[PDB]
Image (cartoon, rainbow, N blue to C red; front, side, top):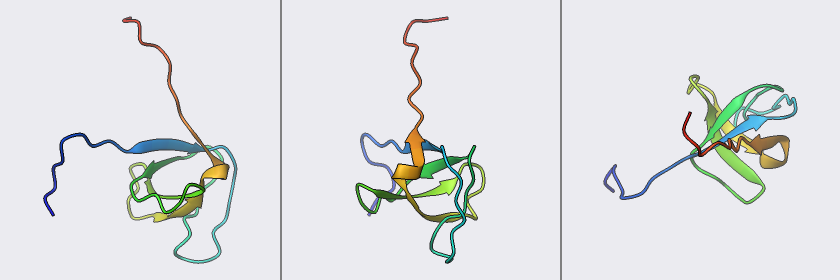
Length: 76
């Protein structure tokens, strides 16, 4: 295992809805937050930590978040 593979990128999303994880494993977030997908569990549930706040890392339902797809290739 070597940290540094040719071609690596994470997935950024935003909590379009609010939620209150009951257990620890589950990540607690609210409408208007960003998550960094690092270890996607399934095609429905992903794993990530609140941007800037790594201390918080738990699985969350992708159906609750929306991948922030920014558009604007043209320069300036």
